[PDB]
Length: 164
Length: 164
Ligand SMILES: [Zn+2]
Ligand SMILES: [Zn+2]
Image (cartoon, rainbow over all chains, first blue to last red):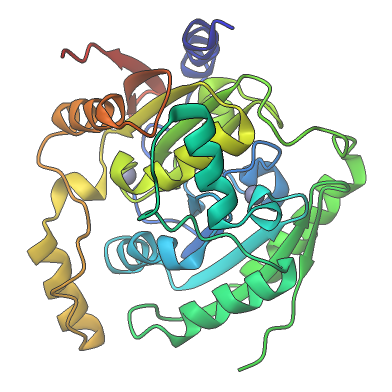
């Protein structure tokens, strides 16, 4: 309930110990990660990344359509060559339709949001297949694209085989 | 040279020792962070977050305009009531213009990206003030918005005063 106070206090400890000031921009692993904003996922901890390893792109659902701007920059300015797409169990984007979220915006804010496309999905493994195939199909994304489901209940990354 | 193999092996060590499987979806701190995908920023270490604390939204430059979809879902489905925006020193989005990036896509892939907006900025502090002011102005975002510069050189978060 004092979030600004808490994160500044923590950051003061982080900076006292900090030794990574000379890391370059371009990610060491030539890797870009796309995943959800979900609070339970520390990407660095889950994948064993360190500072400088991979670009980490996060949005509600980990949607590749919205990650594309960031992935083109990741490859063209950062030299990344590979994408991993990681959707997860118990994702809010599985539970609700565009119409469902628009009703919540009306109820709570009394605002109309009928022109915002919130990009939910109806099946968790389909959404990973769709998002991998999207990036492979894009003329603006180079290199291999691997899909995963992160299991929030176990801490477990599950590779998907995505064809075509 | 084996990113997929390396992340799966690192994930097997993480899962072996994981016991956070019953964390709820809604973030404990009722907080959304918006920052850059930059590989040198571990958000959890920089801010002192643990799994389940805060939604973390990352894109190229940490731009609020693109983060809005994710922020509305964060607040309306995840109960967050606050936003922290963090841009950083040595960001790619400072250095290069839309024309610069479009030219690189033409030179490297042979593609025309003349109708993709990359969301670059011309001044780091100005980028944070525009982004915070953007979210404060939005009828779709509730709560306080605080803006920061993260210094890649010394691990330091610096709060900006943003007027209006
Ligand atoms: Zn999610
Ligand atoms: Zn950046």
